[PDB]
Amino acid sequence: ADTNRTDAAALIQEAYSDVFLDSVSETAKVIGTFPVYNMGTKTTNLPVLSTFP
Amino acid sequence: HAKWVGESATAPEGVKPTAKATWANKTLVAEELAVILPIHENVLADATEDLLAE
Image (cartoon, rainbow over all chains, first blue to last red; front, side):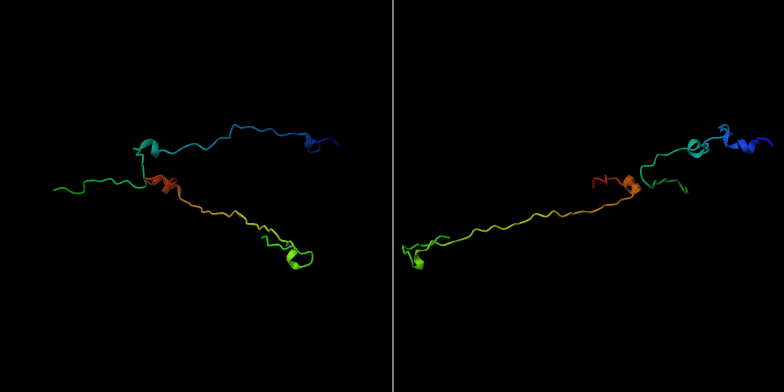
């Protein structure tokens, strides 16, 4: 017989490491790329020329 | 109230009468008036007036 790893297991601690632990990345683009308008109320009206003579 | 009093040693007229004071009680009991006014955050942001002050 011998004292094997399962017999000593109560005094064989595992380690921990963070090399693969990360927060979510911020992937969003549209507010960064397109023109932004600061709205002051729920609705804004945008008039456009529709037809001309 | 007082009475008019006689001078007899034996007749009912000569007796000084007996009488009472009395007190009573009134109470103040406190009672509660209330209301709750709920509003939605976006309505409160989009309105032109300070609706929380209103």
